[PDB]
Amino acid sequence: TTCCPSIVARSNFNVCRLPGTSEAICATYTGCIIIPGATCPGDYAN
């Protein structure tokens, strides 16, 4: 599951993914994170 720290970070993450870039690279690029669970924390609410 991916979690993003802000709305812009999520929007940037979604553009990063369009060419098929791995989630892990889009995470470090945007500040979003990958977690094994499904429940994002309050500081990664977007």
Image (cartoon, helix red, strand yellow):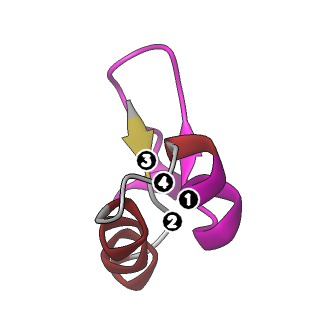
Q: Say which quadrant the N terminus sits in.
A: top left
Q: How many other residues sit within 10 Å of disc 2, few (<14), some (14-19) or many (≥20)?
A: some
Disc number at residue 40? none
Residue drawn at the location 48% of the way across and 54% of the way down: 21
Residue 32 picture location, percent across and down: 55, 57
Q: In which quarter of the image is residue 34?
A: top right
Amino acid type at image mark 2:
Pro
Residue 37 picture location, percent across and down: 42, 14
Q: Do the residues under discs 1 and 4 have CB atoms within 8 angstroms?
A: yes
Secondary element under disc 3, as helix, strand or loop, is strand
Q: Name the residue under label 3.
A: 3
Tell me how far mark 3 sits from mark 2, CA to CA.
Answer: 7 Å
User: Disc count in the image?
Assistant: 4
Q: Name the residue under label 1.
A: 26
Instruction: Compare residues 33 and 17 and report the one nearer the observer.
Output: 17
Instruction: Compare residues 10 and 22 and report the one nearer the observer.
Output: 22
Q: Mark 2 points at which residue?
A: 5
Residue drawn at the location 47% of the way across and 40% of the way down: 41
Q: In which quarter of the image is residue 11?
A: bottom left
Q: Do the residues under discs 3 and 2 have CB atoms within 8 angstroms?
A: yes
Tell me how far mark 3 sits from mark 1, CA to CA.
Answer: 11 Å
Q: Is residue 6 above or below residue 37?
A: below
Q: What stretch is highlighted in magenta?
A: 25-46
Q: Is 40 a magenta residue?
A: yes
Q: How many other residues sit within 10 Å of disc 3, few (<14), some (14-19) or many (≥20)?
A: many
Amino acid type at image mark 1:
Cys
Q: Mark 4 points at which residue?
A: 21
Q: Say which quadrant the C terminus sits in.
A: bottom left
Q: Do the residues under discs 3 and 1 have CB atoms within 8 angstroms?
A: no
